[PDB]
Image (spheres, rainbow, N blue to C red):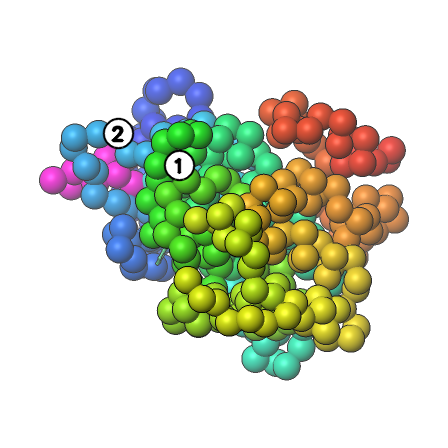
Amino acid sequence: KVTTVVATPGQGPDRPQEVSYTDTKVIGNGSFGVVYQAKLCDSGELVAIKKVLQDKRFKNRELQIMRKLDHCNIVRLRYFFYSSEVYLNLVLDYVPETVYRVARHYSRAKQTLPVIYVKLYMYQLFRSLAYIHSFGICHRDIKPQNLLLDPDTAVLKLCDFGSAKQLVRGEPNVSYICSRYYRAPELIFGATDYTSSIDVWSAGCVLAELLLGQPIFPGDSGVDQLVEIIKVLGTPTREQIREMNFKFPQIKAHPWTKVFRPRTPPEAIALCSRLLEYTPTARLTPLEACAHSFFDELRDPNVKLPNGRDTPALFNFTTQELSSNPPLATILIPPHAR
Ligand SMILES: O=C(Nc1cncc(-c2ccccc2)c1)c1ccnc(NC(=O)C2CC2)c1
């Protein structure tokens, strides 16, 4: 029936409120715990409730990160509450689809996702990355399942901050983060001195996958994944290996244009090659990726969604979001942007 709790709003001062919800059903089970869907009684708005066991010795890192985030391309923490050992419940605004589910529909129908959606989704993913990276926060698990979508508005929201953390130069970090297909080669080599550019490699794998209709670097083991990477980028040099972290197969770099289908836009291929680089510092930053020419169509004042509606918010950048390179506001914010 109706469940009533005293929950603290995600943003603003700590002042708990009585919150009632109903139609509670399980929508996911993972190593962390369970994710439910529920409907708020007052507004009828749908929410996802991520229930995790509370450590007791320390504050939950995912909650601390979520309370600092406020961005149109990041899933909104509406409330949080504790319940029966103690459990933390993160109440997030529900988003009905994911890039994983949508890409699977196109792949099963032997069709590719239209390039207009590839531009819209990748651009919004790079904006969410620019925002979290501006605080030193690395997501560490960028993959299609963590890219929520509203199919009507074409809004994308990054979710699952269970692996996210602030990367401080000089501090070591666990290499065993990030999921199969999307792991940067420095993580496959077990590097503990990686930077936020691991999220950019993962985003590049998502872009290549949306263009190909299948993952670009598949394999259930790191050896297989690394052989697939070497087939595309060629054997990494001794310098490139040192920048990431043995006798590798001497394979020449496959021309990036031949990796994708003939109809693939060349700007999409150019963007891929600048994200999927062995040297972590050579990869584009998320803000530079947003300013790439592959996204120029999104900055045209006449562009509209295939369903006739206007594009979602794309140019409401804040000072925080542009901090890594403020002069890019000239490309990123077009003349017509309000
Ligand atoms: O945070 C959200 N989901 C989430 C977070 N963290 C971990 C998991 C997780 C991981 C492993 C296994 C199982 C679930 C899921 C979340 C928020 C808002 N809306 C949605 N929407 C959906 O799931 C619609 C149906 C596609 C989802």
Residue 327 appearing in the image: yes
Task: State which quadrant residue 262 falls in.
Answer: bottom right
Mark 1 residue's CB less than 8 Å from ligand 1: no
Q: Earlier in the sequence, mark 2 or mark 1?
A: 2
Report the side of 66 relative to 198 (left or right).
left
- Residue type marked 2: Lys
Q: Residue tagged by mark 1? A: 165
x and y percent of residue 4 in the render?
Answer: 27, 38
Closer to the camera in the image, 292 or 243: 243
Q: Is residue 133 left or right of residue 151?
A: left
- Residue shown at 41% from the left, 40% from the top: 193
Tell me, yes or no, whether the highlighted magenta stretch contains residue 85: yes
Query: Between residues 310 and 205, which one lies in front from this camera angle?
Result: 205
> Which of the 4 image quarters holds residue 68?
top left
Name the chief secondary structure element in magenta. strand
- Residue 77: assigned label: none
Position of residue 251 relative to residue 5, above or below, is below
Question: Does the residue tagged 2 have its C-beta within 8 Å of any atom of ligand 1?
Answer: no
Indicate left or right for 32 with 205 as reference: left
- Answer above or below: position of 267 versus 257: above
Residue 59's disc number = 2
State the residue in front, 217 or 263.
Answer: 217
Range shown magenta: 80-89
Question: Mark 2 packing: few (<14 Cα in 10 Å), some, or many (20+)?
Answer: few
Image location (x, y in percent) of residue 331: 80, 36
Q: Secondary structure at mark 1?
A: strand
